[PDB]
Image 1 (cartoon, chains in turn purple, orange):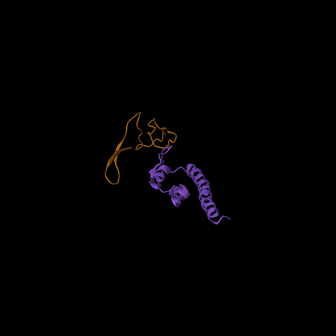
Image 2: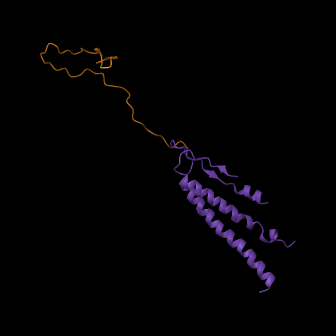
Image 3: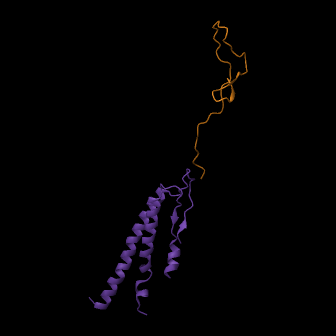
Length: 107
Length: 50
């Protein structure tokens, strides 16, 4: 054993997925006013399987002739949650090397 | 959820009740007693009721 795949766990992939998720939410907020755009959601378990997709969000309310299915209340909350979890993933993956370096150097 | 309902203003019809009659004593003044129309043709030529 003793390999980076096992030392880092899955925290090496989660940081990437949280970046992709943040990009999609940023797209949804920007495309909220453009008619005909369908809100895109990212399935977390899919990138989990890709580590070891880009779906559509069904609206809770009807459109108003635009056909745009973006709820700005939902997007802000989902962007806040993703950003908080992204920082935790950096903390988890960052400490993997800090412990790894301390084991090797002994100091 | 069925929460958004638009409303549009439209003309459902017209009021066809008899108008106010003005007695003028002029020979060439005519008013329709009760319901009825006068058929006339406009500038283009298409006939219509007045």
